[PDB]
Image (cartoon, rainbow, N blue to C red):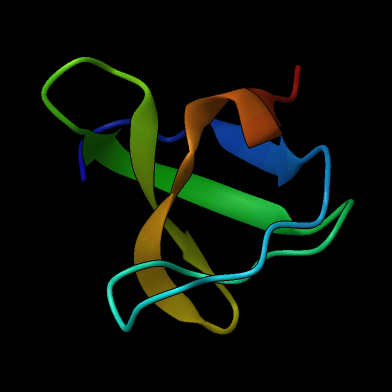
Length: 61
């Protein structure tokens, strides 16, 4: 991606395809970028790369 911000998962999200990424509350993330309306975020966690809903994550200060 482009930006260095740390993000963290606010809620558990379970994937439903091989392009979505399961995340658990409190998990550290990097945001690579966004989908066409910003409502999905492409992220990396320790467990891999894939898409998660944007409202399930938040930047950390």
